[PDB]
Length: 109
Image (cartoon, helix red, strand yellow):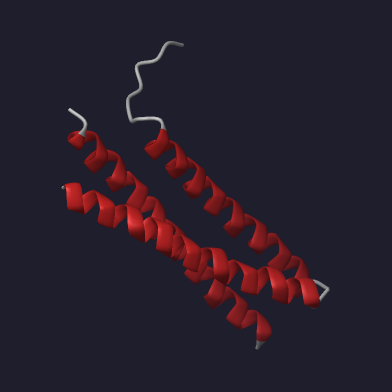
């Protein structure tokens, strides 16, 4: 039952990753309105830091199980580990922008 499980675990990292993406989207609007609540923002930003790290771990578990177990049910995992993993760096890149260099930057072309 290593493979039936490995999906339920992946679909967890998956729906976690949406919670965190759905989240950046509120720390996007909410943050803007401010620039033009103070608590609502610091809360959102903390889930995203934490819930990320949860995900960053459920990933090492996977990275590591694959690695040690190095088939066809394998070749699936290694793939999913990459997909999942990318959609993470995507949500986490997206966010890393939203904050640092202000929403709506006017700076030239």
